[PDB]
Image (cartoon, coloured by chain):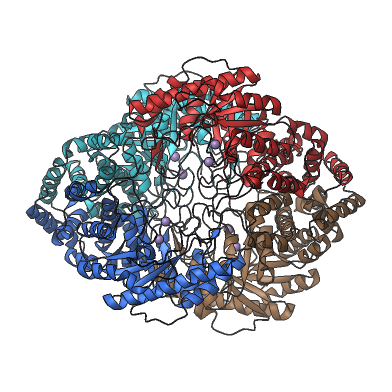
Chain colours: A cyan, B red, C brown, D blue
Amino acid sequence: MVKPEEVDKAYEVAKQRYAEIGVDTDAAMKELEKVPLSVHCWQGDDIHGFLFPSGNYPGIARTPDELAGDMHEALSLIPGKHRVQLHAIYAVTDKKRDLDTLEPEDFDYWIDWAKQEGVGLDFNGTFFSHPMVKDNMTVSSPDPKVRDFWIRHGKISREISNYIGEKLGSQVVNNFWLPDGFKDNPIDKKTPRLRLLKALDEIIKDPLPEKNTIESFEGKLFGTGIESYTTGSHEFYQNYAISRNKLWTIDAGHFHPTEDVSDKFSAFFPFGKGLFMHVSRPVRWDSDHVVIMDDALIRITRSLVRDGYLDRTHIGLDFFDATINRVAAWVVGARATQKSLLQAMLAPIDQLKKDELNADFTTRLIETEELKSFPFGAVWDKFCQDHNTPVGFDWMNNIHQYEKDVQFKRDAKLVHG
Amino acid sequence: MVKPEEVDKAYEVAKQRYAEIGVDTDAAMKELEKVPLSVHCWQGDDIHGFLFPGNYPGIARTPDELAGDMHEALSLIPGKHRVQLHAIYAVTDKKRDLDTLEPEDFDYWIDWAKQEGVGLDFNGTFFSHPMVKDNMTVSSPDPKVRDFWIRHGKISREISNYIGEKLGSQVVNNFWLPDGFKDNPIDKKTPRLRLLKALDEIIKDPLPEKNTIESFEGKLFGTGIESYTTGSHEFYQNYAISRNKLWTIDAGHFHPTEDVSDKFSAFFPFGKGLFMHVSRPVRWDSDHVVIMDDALIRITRSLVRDGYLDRTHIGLDFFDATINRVAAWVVGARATQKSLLQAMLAPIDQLKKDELNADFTTRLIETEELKSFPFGAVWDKFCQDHNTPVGFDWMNNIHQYEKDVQFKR
Amino acid sequence: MVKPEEVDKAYEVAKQRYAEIGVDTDAAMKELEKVPLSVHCWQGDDIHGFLFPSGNYPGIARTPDELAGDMHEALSLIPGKHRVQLHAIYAVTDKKRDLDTLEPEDFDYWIDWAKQEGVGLDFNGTFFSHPMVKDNMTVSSPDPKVRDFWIRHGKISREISNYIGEKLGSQVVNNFWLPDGFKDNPIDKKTPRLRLLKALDEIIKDPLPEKNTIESFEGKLFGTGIESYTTGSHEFYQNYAISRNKLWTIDAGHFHPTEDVSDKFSAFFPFGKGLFMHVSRPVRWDSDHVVIMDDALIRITRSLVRDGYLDRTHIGLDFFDATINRVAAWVVGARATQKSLLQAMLAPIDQLKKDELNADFTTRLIETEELKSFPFGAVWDKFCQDHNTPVGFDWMNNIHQYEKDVQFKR
Amino acid sequence: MVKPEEVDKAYEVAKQRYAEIGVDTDAAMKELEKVPLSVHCWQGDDIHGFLFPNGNYPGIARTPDELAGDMHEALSLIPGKHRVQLHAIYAVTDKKRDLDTLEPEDFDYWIDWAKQEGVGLDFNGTFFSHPMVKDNMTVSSPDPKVRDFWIRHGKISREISNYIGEKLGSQVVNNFWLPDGFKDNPIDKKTPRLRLLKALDEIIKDPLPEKNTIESFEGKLFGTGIESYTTGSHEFYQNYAISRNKLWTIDAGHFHPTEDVSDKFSAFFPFGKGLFMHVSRPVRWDSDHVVIMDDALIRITRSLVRDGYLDRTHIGLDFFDATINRVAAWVVGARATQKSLLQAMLAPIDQLKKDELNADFTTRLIETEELKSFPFGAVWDKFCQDHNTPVGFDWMNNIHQYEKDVQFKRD
Ligand SMILES: [Mn+2]
Ligand SMILES: [Mn+2]
Ligand SMILES: [Mn+2]
Ligand SMILES: [Mn+2]
Ligand SMILES: [Mn+2]
Ligand SMILES: [Mn+2]
Ligand SMILES: [Mn+2]
Ligand SMILES: [Mn+2]
């Protein structure tokens, strides 16, 4: 167990080290406080939800109460104040429901939980794992009956999101992700994107207060069993968001091999409103690995900090690893993102910008490289301790306690509710 | 030497093979006639131009030589096409810099285009100049550098307007900027805001759309500018749509495994027009001669199947000096044409119906069979009908041009 | 229906166009009929096998007799004579078996079928979809019980292979693919590959007649749920094959983005014995799409043909698409491969090589590009007709008849 | 300026943090001392060399003395004991020489400098920038006159390397890199590689003691103007090295998009003798950017120390950036590599290995991620200070002084 006075001592030394290069470590920690991460609920129960009925880790959540407890446990090890992303299938009601019959009140459970937990809520319509998914197509299906069903869900997703936003007093980002596409090479690339354009326009048609909710649109290059064509491409959705004055969702695992998603922000913000940045680790495909401190995460976080885009960018976690402790998964990803944000915030950005404007690329290379071995860990440790979360390896103690007390017994416990 | 009667025989057999699956070979050839390729002048003289004075012999060194080489290439490319000029191909006895060019400096090319019977497209030259400061031009943080290149940009529009008025054919004025960083930048925002402001100033003075319209060409990375490109594909698609201008897709300028044929159907619900630069990247932006490969096949069939040709200008953009430079044009142009023609020789309306009905079996079988249908016999007929040599035969014309012209330089 | 006179006509015109550039179309077709393709049995029944009993196309095979009939139908529409790959889980027996208790006689069904069908057989041990797959590891597992189990199966794959080869009088290529790897970033990359080296050496220890069987070893870059580290890498297996004088398996789906597997042949053969070339279409991952005529297949086929490597290269199909008629999948993939081989064989290779030796890169570019629009289709159509298979679209009639009479009735 | 007592106090605190997770910082720094980096001479003078006399940062070296002084300055800012790589075109002689008439004594200047400086030397034959490069081919050219010329150079590279090895009493790694290939798609892939095999075998024919020199073979996926085919492929050279019992050169910039060269070590060492690891940063192609602390470098260094391959792996620098202070370029790349090696050496590797063997992938993910924010910087700073080099930003002062006193006065 780290000693709190050692953390405080190491922080004063680091603060001095940074002050000597014109960086204020107190101000950097204050900046990190103001960046809430939207923790995805579906990592807790392998995206089962509650609407419809292998070497994976024990302790999967099977009920609202279980998932809520698991997210509370994860959030108690993530320093600061954050948000939670819900999916439509996480509706809590005993009334018989389908995706086109959900009502705002079906999320009262999550509204009450979020108020008592002190987090905001983001929302995702569920356009997958349903018999109305016809040949991998939903909203942009050539079948009018299939299209009309999913348009109904899409409209309902806004109604729910508006209601949640009104009750919490915090704007709900309503994210749209559609599987729509083909496994093999299509003949017609145009007509599916025109069907999508018209169906999306119909979904966002009825006005709702922007203070309560706003829609984001999430593209993808390719998915399993849908590899050759994605109806909702990144180009289609950036165009759609700018044109219809909505948010654009950038998921870090959904782009080309070698594609740096941190390049997109400064090409979008001269034209568009806001982004939903979904941090996710792709390993040679859209594998949805837990977020770690790697090149991609470091570039995403430093690009948002350096160019001042945080107040127009929502940061969400989107990954799914059931092979490890599901609660640990959230905490690794959240801490990875926070410490990368913090490292970016501990740079003398104004002086570096100056040197770069004067084409002093020598200084820029040297300093950026020296900063990677500066004592950013001491500032991170201080941030963890100040927000009553365990430091470094110490949070494994919390995970072992949660495994003994909950996760390793859960499977044998009778589910109820 | 292929016998015309053999071409005619093969064509009649192919015509019947295609008619049996509801494809009209005569109509397919009429469709191909309507697609002019914009042949880039700079392949002729390794992008030297005329403004600022182990490769294959016979490089063009003068306007007349370059004009003669383009005439030779066009004579071996069936149908009617266009030529792309760079600003540095100005023809004048006057002392010019990129900020002092005048429209009449291109009278030479207007006259040549009229006698050759081709339209002209234009490119501002924002590279190979002392005023390129740290690989930046219009979006340079130095106002002296920015103002110089803004003057050149404005002049590129005035030149393009003048050419368009004289030819009575709209000149597409393509903007490509090297602007970016070799290594990792701190500020990605400000360069792109400087670009936005500069481009807006360049296009400020209204010019008739009947004479010219601007297109904007993004890049992922170039040599010595690998880490950041100010003018990104996203920046320019957004810029084109918002400013009601054309977007330039160069097949060589995207990510590994990136399929540029995906972009058309995501652009046209929002945008006005495309300039599609066919170019072959070999593991980087290598500007290899266009060949019949997956990329070209997908580009051409995507434009044909979704009926985007009337809104897509097709230009060649490559540079290979290791081979006969005139041959380079003909290989690239013929690859593009035969690929367009193969796409036009599909029963597209029936295939679309099969696809709407989720008959993915029929789609796979038929698209694979069409790859070995006799599309070559329709291509050969198109070549012959338009007074150009068939197959290997045009190598005779190259060897004669080498002997009589190129090898004598 | 295509008119056979039409085909014969178009062929004679093609024959002359090719003759004019020093290519013999009759000779090219003779070369093609000497290239057997190893048709994978598992496309027919979604790799279910027989050992351990939503937008999926109808008519899936459920029994040996059904799978046998489906492969007979597919082969009937593929011109020339070919081979079939079995997996261990395709054992046909009424006896209680696990992967470590399989007997050669359990493959008597397939030997009898192959002799009647007139095809050779290749083999694959089944190192997946089993409770003894522990944390995605089999032969190279750190758990000795798991190792021993999979080592027993490895040895049995060789024994079965030897028996099939003896009975058929044609060499059985016994292909080893293992899923062994880690989902996330490993600490120790060395020890797993040392465990694999030791285990493989144990599996191939007991000598078996080469005339009957030889082993091939199949690497992978990454798989679903095993993305970060593959124990059996391409580098590992090329080194293992060369050093233990075995075959190396190259699957066209299992390499890096932009990786051209046709580059590997000429870098292997100065050192190595033979290759098992598995044609498979990756679409942005190891997606096992049906093989089509694309840059990869064209480069694979022309690289084998131009450099004379066919006599040392076994060509197998490896793909799994259940979204389309499963019998059609076989025929599309096989015809695409043969088409692409034939186009390679229809080039003036000796003259092009001389042009290249003299650095005449102009002639090489012009000619290779012109050959892409030469009437190779007319020669392919002739090959199809000569070997009593339908021409072009026509074989769709056979699929519709097989759907009505057999597939749609299951 | 950093205060030595402040570095020492921060080190003692870090020592304690690492001791508590079973890591010995003092031992970790001793392990780092034993990894010499082979600093490439050609970054100093834009690969001009001296043999054939004939936008960019000022102060390029133009003479042996200027280059020697620049490498001395760079080494003075890189903590510990390292090596220098020479190219054959860095011959120092007033005699009229071609690449096929170089003599060992032509390198006496560099032997004398290395003895003075207290560093070992590695060597590279120069198979580029010469009229005898015919259609981008050298050793494996279809022209027997071209082949024979370059084979003469290849034999001479071994004779030079043996001589240097003897004089310095330190084995010279003689690295072979050939541009040989095609710009566009070849018809015949087989024959070029059979020509290469035959030519390499003739080059290494004459026996020389391993004690003085051993050959390494460097492959490439593609180069500028040689994009479509490389005769000397990675597969060809790994097979060649294992077969002929020589070293295999892995250059981090010469592989496919997304390729992780750190994967290759554990697939090589069950079969082969040794590696020459050229650290180099590719940015979307073989761009030869200065090495920085990124995923690739972190994976290369941790893969070598985790699996205990350092005693069989020579680490060399290979990059060329003339847009920045050329001496600075060396220090950035060397320090990136050392701090990355050091971080990997500061992990509880035995415990992590045990956890992994026991399939505790939860613990492995948590711990590896926590280690990335442990105070490795305080250990790095201690290593820098202990070895009489400036800490953190401080060495920018030395660069500015060297610009003022030496570099900016040259041009
Ligand atoms: Mn997402
Ligand atoms: Mn994902
Ligand atoms: Mn272009
Ligand atoms: Mn280009
Ligand atoms: Mn395979
Ligand atoms: Mn596969
Ligand atoms: Mn190197
Ligand atoms: Mn390099």
Instruction: Say which of C56 and D165 sits in front.
Output: D165
The residue lying at 60 percent from left, 31 percent from top is B84
Q: Position of residue C73 (x, y in %)?
A: 78, 59
Along the horizontal axis of the image, is D171 left or right of D207?
left
Residue B352 location, quadrant: top right
Residue C89 location, quadrant: bottom right
The reply to whether residue A102 is visible in this rendering is no
Instruction: Say which of A358 and B354 sits in front.
Output: A358
Is C130 situated above or below B408? below
Q: Position of residue A80 (x, y in %)?
A: 24, 38
Along the horizontal axis of the image, is D392 left or right of A55?
left
Is A393 situated above or below C41? above
The reply to whether residue D154 is visible in this rendering is yes
The residue lying at 25 percent from left, 34 percent from top is A354
Task: Name the quarter where the C terminus of chain B is drawn.
Answer: top right
Instruction: Say which of A283 and D383 sits in front.
Output: D383
Toward the right, the furthest residue is C5
Q: Position of residue A192 (x, y in %)?
A: 62, 32
Instruction: Say which of C112 and D88 sits in front.
Output: D88
